Image: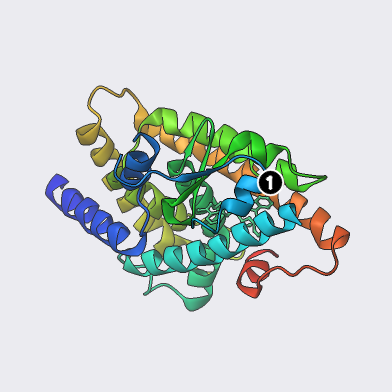
Amino acid sequence: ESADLRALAKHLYDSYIKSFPLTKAKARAILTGTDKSPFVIYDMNSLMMGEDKIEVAIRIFQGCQFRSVEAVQEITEYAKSIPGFVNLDLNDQVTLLKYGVHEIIYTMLASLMNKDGVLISEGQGFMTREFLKSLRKPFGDFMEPKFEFAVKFNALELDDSDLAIFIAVIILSGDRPGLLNVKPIEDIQDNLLQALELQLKLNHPESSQLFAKLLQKMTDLRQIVTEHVQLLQVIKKTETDMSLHPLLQEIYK
Ligand SMILES: CN(CCOc1ccc(C[C@H](Nc2ccccc2C(=O)c2ccccc2)C(=O)O)cc1)c1ccccn1
């Protein structure tokens, strides 16, 4: 019944606001500004001005590494609020997070992107696309495909209350490898999808088949993950002196 699906949409949006400090609504108010504009990093010595105000490639790398660990933590916190998730088998909870976390991270990374760059340091800074692309060897190809995804994903014009449900749909997948009790996962996702469908029709009545278009976007996410794991493997063997944070490599197996 629609009333129960509305209250579940309200619950998830509420918990999303509580778990994710930098929302898309805030991200967009910073990107389209004049209260607190970001400091813009576009070359090497602007990057070096970027702590008088808020190698280089390695520096950026470990900066993203720190933020991803922080994102995993926020995502993990959000997961526990999805009704039914903490009642699943422990191994399955772990499995849903291990595989869901980077697809969520690229989804929400789009919230901080326009075609020209990405918000960093809680929105305090803005790093340009072209500067990320000019990085040496393998580092300069990490962010470009996420920019590509974001440009297209942001075309859907989703807002945070949309994203809160869609992110929950991602986590409760059920075709993740190694799941022990697929079926109670699928019964939750099914209710989520019902919530997402009603949420999209009410929030975007003019937007024909946004539900279908949003779900098709889940193949775009799966592909970014794969590219990324390959690039991460090239680096593990090029700079044997540099370490992936244990939360992150645990996820990567
Ligand atoms: C908010 N934000 C953007 C987050 O961007 C992300 C962009 C991508 C990711 C996924 C993340 N990838 C990395 C993990 C460890 C080290 C580097 C990376 C890459 O990301 C990378 C490598 C080389 C060059 C550029 C990126 C993951 O797999 O956990 C996570 C986050 C910030 C904030 C502060 C500093 C940098 N940004």
- The residue located at (53%, 75%) in the rendering is 91
Query: For numbered disc 1, what is the local secondary structure?
Result: helix
Q: Position of residue 129 (x, y in %)?
A: 60, 36
Q: Toward which corner of the image does residue 215 lie, by quadrant?
A: top left
Instruction: Please state the horizontal and vertical placement of residue 211, each as a whole percent of the image.
Output: 36, 34
Q: Horizontal and vertical percent for residue 149?
A: 55, 35
Which quadrant does the C terminus fall into?
bottom right
Q: Residue at x 12, y 49 (%)?
A: 3
Direction from residue 2 to residue 105 in the image, left or right: right
**Amino acid at circle 1:** Met
Name the foreground residue: 126 vs 253.
126
From the viewer's perspective, is 141 left or right of 114?
right
Let me know if residue 177 appears in the view.
no
**What colour scheme governs how the chains and residues are painted in the rendered image of this protein?**
rainbow
Q: In this view, does 53 lie to the left or right of 42?
A: left
Mark 1 nearby-residue class (10 Å; few <14, some 14–19, many ≥20): few
Q: Ligand 1 is found in which quarter of the picture? A: bottom right
Res 236 → quadrant: bottom right
> Where 162 sits versus 116, above or below?
below
Mark 1 beta carbon near ligand 1 (under 8 Å): no
From the viewer's side, name the closer residue of 170 and 133.
133
Q: Mark 1 points at which residue?
A: 44
Q: Residue 229 in the image: state x and y as whole percent.
A: 71, 53
